[PDB]
Image (spheres, coloured by chain):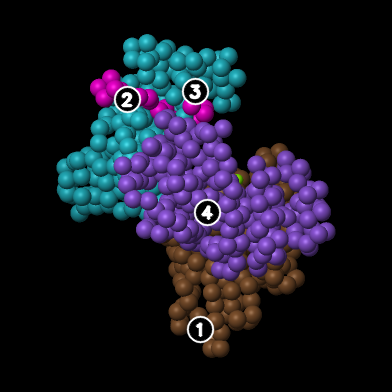
Chain colours: A purple, B brown, C cyan
Amino acid sequence: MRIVAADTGGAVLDESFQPVGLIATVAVLVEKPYKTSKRFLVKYADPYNAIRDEIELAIELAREVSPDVIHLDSTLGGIEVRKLELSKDLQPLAKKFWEETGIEIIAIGKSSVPVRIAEIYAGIFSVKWALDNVGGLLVGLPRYMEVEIKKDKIIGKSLDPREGGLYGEVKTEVPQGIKWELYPNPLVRRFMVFEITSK
Amino acid sequence: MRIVAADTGGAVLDESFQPVGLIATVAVLVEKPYKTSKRFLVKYADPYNYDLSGRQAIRDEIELAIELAREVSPDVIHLDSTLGGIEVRKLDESTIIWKELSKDLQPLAKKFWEETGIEIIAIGKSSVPVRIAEIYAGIFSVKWALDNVGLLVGLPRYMEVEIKKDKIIGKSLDPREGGLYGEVKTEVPQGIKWELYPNPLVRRFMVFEIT
Amino acid sequence: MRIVAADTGGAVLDESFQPVGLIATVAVLVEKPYKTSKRFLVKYADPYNYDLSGRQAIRDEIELAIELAREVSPDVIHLDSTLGGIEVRKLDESTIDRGKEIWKELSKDLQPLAKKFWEETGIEIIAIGKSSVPVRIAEIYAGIFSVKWALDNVGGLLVGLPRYMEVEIKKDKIIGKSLDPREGGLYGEVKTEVPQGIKWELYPNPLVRRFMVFEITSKS
Ligand SMILES: [Mg+2]
Ligand SMILES: [Mg+2]
Ligand SMILES: [Mg+2]
């Protein structure tokens, strides 16, 4: 099965580890064996000042790759959004999109692996954003994921082995003259902080 | 202590990764140090003609638990019903989906308690032996798929299997549970192949695909 | 950010695996990268003489946190009560609005303590509870100290550890570690002299999934 999903993640934190705003909305194409995505879109929000932005970006990707279904971040047991819970706002959108493409948009939320994969990529693109904006940043990553930074790419991985080894990967130019570290958010258990400093 | 628990796990999936029915119901005997079971029973259902509501599974679960309990005489029976550890023979609408299911479990547990003095408790996901039964269910579902294959089998929550020449090993993927596992002797056919990968519809659940 | 937190954990269990009482209350100083504590205080209860209202525990927790905070001067104290991070100074019955009904009896003891300590220092005590990593680290240390207590106080003893943690025994120390990799590798170490004539085993609590049992048995 080919699935398009979307989620928003990554948060700019203040000096007291309190979130200012979210960083990245990502749409991903996920196919078997459903551990990662090689095909995705990113929309950077403005962190320093929603489910709609996810569903829109998902639709944009779906028209490009023609998936079997779209997963949205709403936990409703996988019910088709056109056959519908604030996400009733998206029912008419789900209705007309199905009529146009034959693609079902389903409210599966936290039960969805592709949504989780989209979330991991949001974390990765949040780090990329940090790499490309850093004199010091605190980025709050999505729940239990870590990143590795190599010369030409960032790797994202879920910390939960129960998820079966979900991961992400984004090629990007990693600048010299930076210092990064990764550590637990003291205020939010199971969430990691990506702190970066320009040398 | 000596505990008997039961559960039903393993689901034949369709093309849309949605379950058509359940496969294996297992009763286990668990003793110290409570990581696995050396003594267990299994009952297979018909997955292609299954009561997906849950009534059938829980009936099979309590019947099979009782049966194993008669043989091994455990201190107590754990049922996969997350209701605070209350005795099933006292399950009323008052003490409380499960209201309906209590209707066909309460008299049965009451009868069994009168025969044996052994309580059947609705402890559910708080029970390690229940979880061990669930893991064995996944193992027996995989054994079943090895004998009825192609197939798409949805495994119980966060567990994987390894397939040897002479046995199937199941293990929890959650290290927080403390290394829960199970083994089942079996033979493995020729002219087949299998993969284990995330169920894209059910986070933290794995899929066993075989051809 | 430098944080002092406290929690009470570790339980003497009966052979039906039910807690008789809690053992250790621990206050910890936690600094970046917030994985462990190298500065901590411990107070032992009597598990056989224990109040599971939780009143005695939260009282012990706050006073021990304050005592430690006076010596290390943290930016903030984390208390294990999950209320969203409200300052305990401002914890009145008006602000509370059975969870509500319970914390208004406790507020009569907690609020003035927090108030007095803030006036002295400007340091806030926040009711953050379970989302706090330093609280979790305190909990891990409580599990460690409960084992140390059990080692010193045993012909057999079942120690119920706090949720998903293990302990390792070394010749000169006890190590505690979270079993949840999602927490990023939280742990703690306490130096002790391990007594002879005893054996130990770590295994799952069959009645409480994700809780381990540390059982000690006298030798010979
Ligand atoms: Mg979301
Ligand atoms: Mg069950
Ligand atoms: Mg506590």
Same-chain check, marks 3 and 2: yes
Which amino acid does the dot numbered 3 rest on?
Ile
Q: Amino acid at mark 4?
A: Tyr
Which residue is denoted by mark 3 in the rendering? Answer: C86
Name the chain letter of the residue that bears numbered label 4.
Answer: A
Mark sitting on residue B187? 1
- Residue denoted by label 4: A121
Query: Viewed as shown, does residue A179 lie left or right of C112?
Result: left
Residue nearer the viewer, B32 or C83: C83
User: Which one is earlier in the sequence, the residue at label 3 or at label 2?
Assistant: 2
Camera-nearest label, 1 or 4: 4
Asked whether the residues under the numbered discs 3 and 2 touch, taking CB atoms below 8 Å apart as contact, a structural biologist would say no
User: On the image, numbered disc 2 is attached to which residue?
Assistant: C74
Q: Which chain does the residue under circle 3 lie in? A: C
x, y percentage for residue B54? 70, 58
Query: Helix or strand or loop: what does disc 3 sit on?
Result: strand
